[PDB]
Image 1 (cartoon, rainbow over the protein chains, first blue to last red):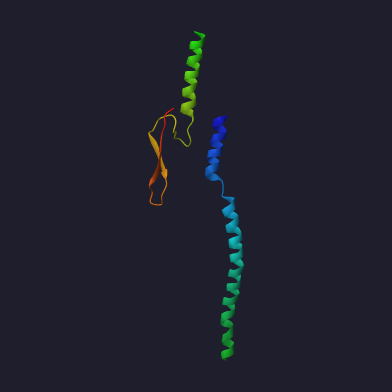
Image 2: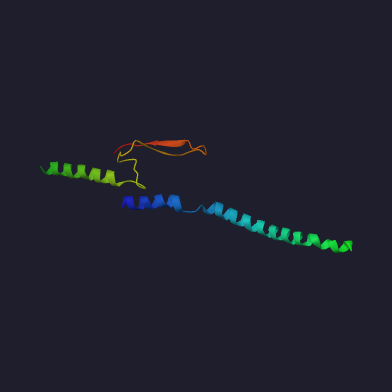
Amino acid sequence: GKLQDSLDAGVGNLVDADLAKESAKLQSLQTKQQLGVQALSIANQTPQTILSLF
Amino acid sequence: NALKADFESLRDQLQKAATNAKFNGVSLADGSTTKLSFLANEDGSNFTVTAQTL
């Protein structure tokens, strides 16, 4: 009974995720994504001004 | 003789507890090996953990 839950803790040290860094990176990437969409829209608008030349 | 048989049983259970306690195919208690050397640096210098036979 000692060895079973000891090995369970041992696999838990190896497989389990670090939830705090995962949350930090999750909202970090989410805030980055909207700025990426804004950069996409601006890059699409950059060619639009060629019409003013003619 | 009864106390001697108790001594034999506890002595055998000591080996049964020592040999079977091993994580991932290796142990620091059974004495099968002198040391384990886990990583400590990006260079690869190991954190030596000397085995203590039980």
